[PDB]
Amino acid sequence: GSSGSSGRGSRFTWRKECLAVMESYFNENQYPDEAKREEIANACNAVIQKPGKKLSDLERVTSLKVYNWFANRRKEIKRRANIAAILESSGPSSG
């Protein structure tokens, strides 16, 4: 990745456009219902969907993809609030 302990992207990528929409829904609801996930996911695909161009699975944002990103944030925020780890650990993570 570029920044953040988060990465290991599985043959996928998160565009700034799709990231802005995901953050919006997360602000209103941490856990977007099934229908909510599709609503937000669809918007992400549109913001990226270009005229005369074809969308690829690499940019395609499905309901499952949205949940994966949301879960990463919830766990990332909750993990920082708990930090139930004392043992030694070598991580590049910053801040």
Image: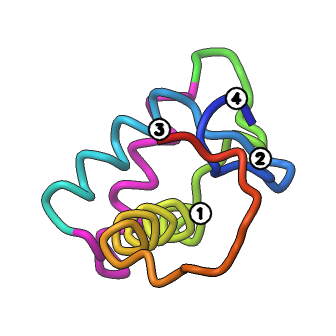
Depicted 24 relative to depicted 20: above or below: below
Going by the numbered disc 1, the residue's amino acid type is Lys
**Distance (Cα) linking label 3 and label 4:** 17 Å
Going by the numbered disc 4, the residue's amino acid type is Ser
Q: Is residue 87 magenta?
A: no
Pointers 2 and 1 in contact (C-beta within 8 Å): yes
For marks 4 and 1, the one nearer the N-term is: 4
**Distance (Cα) linking label 2 and label 1:** 10 Å
Label 3: which secondary element: helix
Residue found at the far left of this picture: 28
Mark 2 neighbour density, 10 Å: few (under 14) some (14–19) many (20 or more): few
Q: Nearer the viewer, residue 3 or 67?
A: 3
Pointers 3 and 4 in contact (C-beta within 8 Å): no
The residue carrying mark 3 is 18
Pointers 1 and 3 in contact (C-beta within 8 Å): no
For marks 2 and 4, the one nearer the N-term is: 4
Q: Position of residue 59 (x, y in %)?
A: 68, 40
Q: Which mark is residue 26?
A: none
Asked which colour scheme the image uses, the reply is rainbow
For marks 3 and 4, the one nearer the N-term is: 4
Q: Position of residue 5 (x, y in %)?
A: 64, 49
Label 4: which secondary element: loop
Seen in the image, is 77 located left or right of residue 9? left
Magenta segment: 30-49
**Distance (Cα) linking label 4 and label 1:** 20 Å
The residue carrying mark 2 is 12
**Distance (Cα) linking label 2 and label 3:** 12 Å
Q: Position of residue 73 (x, y in %)?
A: 42, 61
Of the residues tagged 2 and 4, which is closer to the observer? 4
Residue drawn at (43%, 73%) of the image: 79
